[PDB]
Amino acid sequence: GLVPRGSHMWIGVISLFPEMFKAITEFGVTGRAVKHNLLKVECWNPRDFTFDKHKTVDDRPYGGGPGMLMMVQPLRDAIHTAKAAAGEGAKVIYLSPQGRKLDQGGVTELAQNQKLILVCGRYEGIDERLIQTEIDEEWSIGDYVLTGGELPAMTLIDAVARFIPGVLGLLDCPHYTRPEVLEGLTVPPVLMSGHHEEIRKWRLKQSLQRTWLRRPELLEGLALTDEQRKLLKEAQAEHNS
Amino acid sequence: GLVPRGSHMWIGVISLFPEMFKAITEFGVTGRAVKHNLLKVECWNPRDFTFDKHKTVDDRPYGGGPGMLMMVQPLRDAIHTAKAAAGEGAKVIYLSPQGRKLDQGGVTELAQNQKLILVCGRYEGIDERLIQTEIDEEWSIGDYVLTGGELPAMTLIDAVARFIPGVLGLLDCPHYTRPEVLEGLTVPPVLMSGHHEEIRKWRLKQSLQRTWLRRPELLEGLALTDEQRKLLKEAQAEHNS
């Protein structure tokens, strides 16, 4: 086709609930990426790597406490099988609130990988030593507590999928569509003017203003263009007075 | 049963892909919460609120550009039906990267709501005016770009579900489980000592140290106990020298 070979992204997933990933493999743009063979998601379930009659996948933490942990053997073995399939150059990622905070910059660098293996924890997490022996990088999608690593893993896949060849910075400017007047609220006249240039500048100005007011941190680390600086300056002055 | 009536949580969801929510309603603790009638998730799809032959749910942005937006009428009407079902006291939430940053403190306050309606956007988002007429609060799960609001919505549900009566702060201390020696790596002796007190202190110290090194921001805004301050001080001194 139009896309060169060897540009597809492969993602191995270790999870007790592989079916959860249908949420991204069967719907929307990510689902389309999978259908078009641009994105490949392969899952392995630790429950299939047990040897006891009850397929036990959890274990007690040393030191005591009610906080269960994933059983090491089934989880490690699942990882080993994924690594066997992925072969060379496969970064193993563990999703947890103690990992590096994910942001668009992080998504960009993770997307540079053609192969990734995502480890989804349940219970209170996984053995600290496994982080040392099997995990390459630990990442957190946010500072909040979740019941498992599956949502964080799917969030990561969704974010990086947008960087896959064949698939299709600051806070967005306000957006408007029909009707022209919604419950008495009108669309900014400039957007109805047809003046391509005035519209481009208005949108940029609004984007900068909103980023400044809501996420000023995103501005730090980016040397804005001369135009952006001028528009932002105007917005800041107008906001105050 | 043991749980008093009127303590269950209801969550209405507006999404073009209702099936994605099976990821949380059919698996793990959230799935168990749904099975035990502790959590209720009801979805409405804008596609069911259209009147044209092609069930159109997207529309062109005023001002031009390739960035499509959700069509106002089907989306607004879906919201109205959810509000009709939810009745009184139902906060409507829009998930977007321009919303308030979600953190455990935010999860705690959102969990105080017995009813919530989550609006999941697709395309480039929704009309700015709808945020004014139908949305009560805007929330962001992180500073990264996603293909839709469904994962953010499920992440929010998962986080607040943990606060539901009947269901079951800083970075966790390292955790360990069998075997005692994993690929030559041993479990900290204190955890194998059986000394309940030494273990409690060791774990707290490690939790504080890790929070300090990886997420010092979490410390800001919390007046630690005398013990925590002592252990953290020791950890900081040991880390340096």
Image (cartoon, coloured by chain):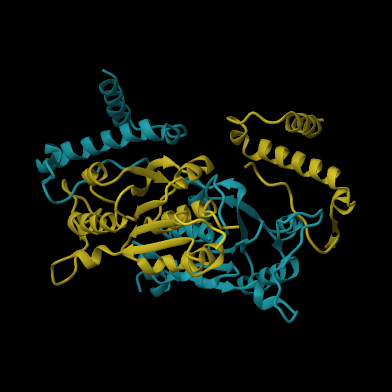
Chain colours: A yellow, B cyan
Image quadrant assignment for residue A132: top left
| Residue occupying image coordinates x 71% and y 42% | A207
Q: Nearer the viewer, residue A104 or A98?
A: A104
Does A29 sit above or below residue B227?
below
Q: Nearer the viewer, residue A34 or A70?
A: A34
Task: List x then y, in percent, for residue A195.
Answer: 88, 48
Residue found at the very far top of the displayed protein: B241
Does B120 sit above or below residue B17?
above
Asked whether the viewer can see residue B3, the reply is no
Quadrant into which the C terminus of chain A falls: top right
How many numbered marks appear? 0
Q: Nearer the viewer, residue B85 or A110?
A: A110
Does A231 sit above or below residue B142?
above
Image quadrant assignment for residue A220: top right
Q: Is residue B50 left or right of residue B62?
A: left
Q: Is residue B189 left or right of residue B208?
A: left
Task: List x then y, in percent, for residue A8.
Answer: 46, 57
Task: List x then y, in percent, for residue A186.
Answer: 86, 56
Q: Is residue B103 left or right of residue B234?
A: right
| Residue occupying image coordinates x 30% and y 49% | A88
Q: Nearer the viewer, residue B70 or A109?
A: A109
Q: Is residue A8 left or right of residue B78?
A: left
Residue found at the very far bottom of the displayed protein: B53
Quadrant into which the N terminus of chain A falls: bottom right
Task: List x then y, in percent, for residue B42.
Answer: 54, 73
Asked whether the viewer can see residue B180, the reply is yes
